[PDB]
Image (cartoon, coloured by chain):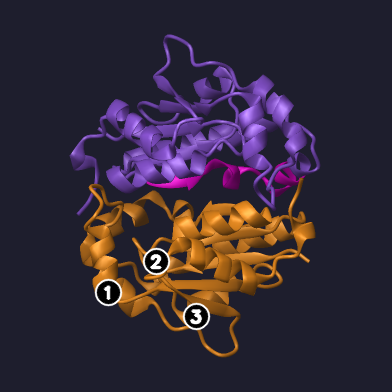
Chain colours: A orange, B purple
Amino acid sequence: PTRHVVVMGVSGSGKTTIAHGVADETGLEFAEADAFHSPENIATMQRGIPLTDEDRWPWLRSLAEWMDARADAGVSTIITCSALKRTYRDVLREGPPSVDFLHLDGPAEVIKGRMSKREGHFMPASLLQSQLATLEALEPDESGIVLDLRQPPEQLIERALTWLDIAPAVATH
Amino acid sequence: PTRHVVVMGVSGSGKTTIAHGVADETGLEFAEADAFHSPENIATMQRGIPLTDEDRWPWLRSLAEWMDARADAGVSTIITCSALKRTYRDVLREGPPSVDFLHLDGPAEVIKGRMSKREGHFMPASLLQSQLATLEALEPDESGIVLDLRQPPEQLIERALTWLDIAPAVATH
């Protein structure tokens, strides 16, 4: 079967590093979910305005559809997403036959410290509060694990890989 | 003005690391170009069949359109692409007001050695020969620099950042 992984966490949590590390060892196709947003939604967030559920539904559906179409062609995927509510994850699960979540997170103060070590930001620091409010804990009937971003990425990637147990036959050589 | 960067190089050259490193310091929006391919085109390549010019035109146009629409909303971008011909780069340049290329490359034997250190592969090693044939050198009237993948990524990212000279006002805080 195909596998479909979502790395979920706020901006500056290190999602790209984790997703990329997982992809490189499993053959999963990596994609960045923000690229699926409309340009206007990206611009709105860049000015510091949080999106609503209504803003996000078409985006979530396009992600679900992209994963479903990849699945149909035998392609396994891993995508990075910003904060998701439980209902948002429900929409993602409407696409491909399964979705496994890696929830990358940690104390707000550590996240803020990470962001302070960068010159450029794609998203404003002011969005962090609203994002942490949007990020709903994984619930018992979902498939996912938490990755504490205070740990080194190499450890988190190994932890993810052990949990995901992606079948070797998913990759290519 | 908005900026639009393409990191071009074959699979396993380290494009994601470079693009991600540049994005993190400039605020450029990172996207992976393969996600814009149709599922069937991804599957075709995964079986080891190289795409043709005809297969690639709609993909290149969608990348150009995505960059143009981001530009219109004031959003600067950096994307990773596999091997591109000069004519392919012409199509990318039909979109946004400018495109700067970072050409990540090196000897085939070094690329093959990098790929051998990974368990999973998104694309088969057999595609490398055809990709190296498709990757046409940057020409004098194009905007780009070569990044030798034998160098450490930290050095290449600094080299890219110095050359790109992304205005600080492109980012957010």
Residue bearing mark 3: A87
> Mark 2 against mark 3, which lies toward the viewer?
3
Q: Residue at x 35, y 27 (%)?
A: B97
On the rendered structure, is A53 left or right of A116? right
Image coordinates for residue B70, horizontal then vertical, percent:
38, 42
Residue contact at pointers 1 and 3, CB within 8 angstroms: no
Q: Which amino acid type is shown beneath numbered disc 2?
A: Asp
Residue bearing mark 1: A108
Q: Residue at x 31, y 33 (%)?
A: B161
Q: Which amino acid type is shown beneath numbered disc 3?
A: Thr
What chain letter is assigned to the residue under label 1? A
Residue bearing mark 2: A55
What chain letter is assigned to the residue under label 2? A
Q: Which region shows up in magenta? A: B29-43
Q: What is the C-alpha distance between the residues marked 2 and 1?
A: 25 Å
Q: What is the C-alpha distance between the residues marked 2 and 3?
A: 14 Å
